[PDB]
Image (tube, rainbow over all chains, first blue to last red; front, side):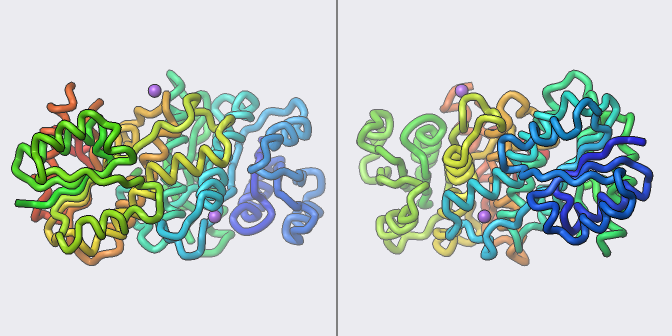
Amino acid sequence: MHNVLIVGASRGIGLGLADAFLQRGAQVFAVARRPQGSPGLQALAERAGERLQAVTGDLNQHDCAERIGEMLGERRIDRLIVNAGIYGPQQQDVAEIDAEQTAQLFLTNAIAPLRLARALSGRVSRGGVVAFMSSQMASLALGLSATMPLYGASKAALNSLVRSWEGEFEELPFSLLLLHPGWLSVEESAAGLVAAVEDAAGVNACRFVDYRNQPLPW
Amino acid sequence: MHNVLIVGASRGIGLGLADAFLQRGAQVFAVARRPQGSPGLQALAERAGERLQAVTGDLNQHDCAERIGEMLGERRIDRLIVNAGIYGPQQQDVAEIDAEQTAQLFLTNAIAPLRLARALSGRVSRGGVVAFMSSQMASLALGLSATMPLYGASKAALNSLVRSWEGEFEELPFSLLLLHPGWLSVEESAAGLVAAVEDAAGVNACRFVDYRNQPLPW
Ligand code: NA
Ligand code: NA
């Protein structure tokens, strides 16, 4: 029984990831801003009982790792998954975006995910996996982000920070994944990403992969 | 006689680029926050006479394209070079950076450069070149940004936005360059980048290159 921490597990792929890991026999620690006000998560929690724990926690708060920390207690994290991404302004227009919006977009999509993962890094199992929800829109080589440039740039920044983190170690103590979930049901996506996550266990590599475990170019 | 616009031309590579293009026989329009308080630019201006025009202009202001616009008049831009770039916080620490700092770093290094270039795009000659000062630190493949992750991420975001812009056209109307200046004197770097810029003229390609016109991987 591996311990899996999902930050952003209230709805969508996050909730799907929690279900997919539960089905693989993991102990799952689900973090969300308002866990009680997600009917999906609550119902998932009440099926399988103690094996899914809901935790209040906002990635954007500076006390987030501490709240997760005291809650975990002594147990180590085998799989850490940071799923907290926003689109940015609807218009995705560089001419219209203000400072507040810029701060929010890059804090939420890039900076805060690294802040959390670094704070918890000491508690992740050696040969475990730390994975971040990214996007194919982050890929410079693919250059597919014309219709949502600000979103794609926020995710390129995420990818950059994660590659930079890998650059700090002589050898990685765990794997660093950047995940493209696809756009395809939530269940198909989640099942695939879990497979991709589990494939990286014990390899201690930095990879950018989709829900099929295919390498995306940077 | 080609018209060359350099945004950020008071000091460093910017000033070097202005000199390098002047020596190749161009009409050069230099923009800077404080043109009068740069002894280099003033002395460069006085040597070339009318062939170098200094203009007050801050890339981060929303009226910047308008000020450049009225000043150019009807003249088309053959080469547009956006030379902006700040380091970000000294500590380069995701755990310490606030909203103000985040806004400033991504506005300055990524968003404002695209805002300006897009606003002036209509006035760039077809088969001309729009170039942005980037960094080898933007390269995910090279992964050299461990010691300055926020800087590198800001530049990866720049690269992303430029690739996204390329993605809007069926075929590019001009070249989109991302330049690594290579830290080597200002004159050697500037001469090389000018060669790289001029090599892209008439090709209408998106390229990430250094001062030797060598491709950097994304
Ligand atoms: Na926003
Ligand atoms: Na420095």
